[PDB]
Image (cartoon, rainbow, N blue to C red; front, side, top):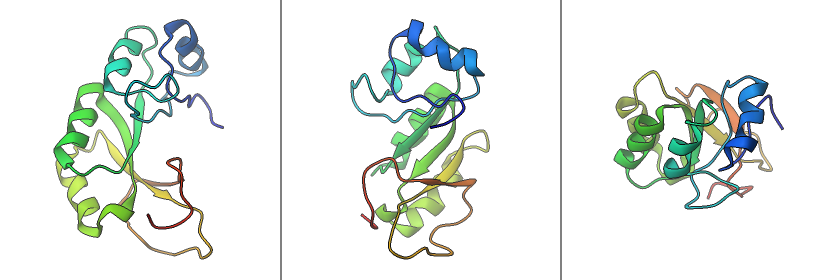
Length: 134
């Protein structure tokens, strides 16, 4: 678990608990209309209830769609599943301003690679299901 990192919560009365915990940032992923994973749409509502900062974990095809979220909600970080493509990650940081960072979702594998994708702000675990590079 974490400091105040809660997964999609669309109840302001509920979300305020993380904001009250620090309003630092929450740990939500953009799963379309899930009450366990918040997407841009709930988040924008949620930020009117509990002004907590947002993060995202997504293997996106389009960089502009990541930029969209990074901009709209104003994220802090975004977790890229580097498995999508190597140069893709290298591209994200160019589009994404220094206000939003990138963390590399390190999936738990049999081997621990020293370097997979770097120039990322932080290394975190995989929260998108997987124990391999897929």
